[PDB]
Length: 379
Image 1 (spheres, rainbow, N blue to C red):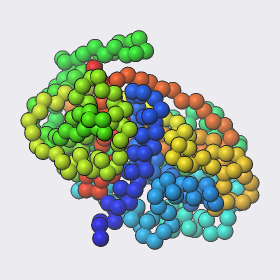
Image 2 (image 1 turned 90 degrees about the vertical axis):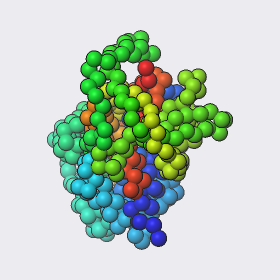
Image 3 (image 1 turned 45 degrees about the vertical axis):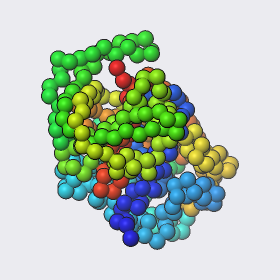
């Protein structure tokens, strides 16, 4: 049989890429950075706290049940493999559950959560609003090595909050072949918002794994693999041949299996690679993307079912979000993501940025885990 971490990595990545797809289809040329692994991690925990049809919708969308034989163990084996020193490049991931101290939990829940996730439920008092907000924000800052410090703004949680599920993901890698200094090769970028920014354009000519594919409508696109120095992780970069072809032509067919096929079809060939040196930070609302995949019950006040956690009072999801930051330069890439599901009663808005972009995917190849992916503005 296949290496177990590779099987669950595929389920997690396929689910996460489908969520990204809904995000892409909703806003033409959106500039955003995202983490498929991060969203899969938090929704895996959500499986244990929900029940009835709310839990059934999540399990159907993810393709597995967290408590079925071998699933939790294989997921644990997977994160240990991602974080191992043998990767050379560094990955850190941590999950946590924060629950209201006076919410009576159902018999067996806490010990079962510990058995599957090897972690205990962190109890806090959301009635001390600012103290609770600080506890969660400080935890996130620590587990993202200081990259994401204010995940929860004032008002995100309050005395009505009862549960907060979070995943913190950090990645720091060096290119196998660094780019030469790009500080004298800046270029003007004219945004649709009317402003203009100056961006260093990094460049190098060498042999890279590369391949060409076509969409269902016969449109061609280039795909190049840029490896990190431990040779287990890499960044795939994709863009259409013709500036006339919209990026949606690629994103409307994206999947974990497709990305696997890209890798399997590559040939090491000479190429001139040009990549901008930049920093991008975005925050995405996951409500509609998740509803679009079938998980509608969890967001409805009187329909949601959290009886696997508590039968003391009705509960539903008020907010589901992901904050991500990425930095790309001549030496490498540093990226962090914090995903959270907040059970309370107050939701928030989302800000959207748009400009014709290219696509990128950061992947751990030995297991096929898709850690980060995004759309970045092209010159």
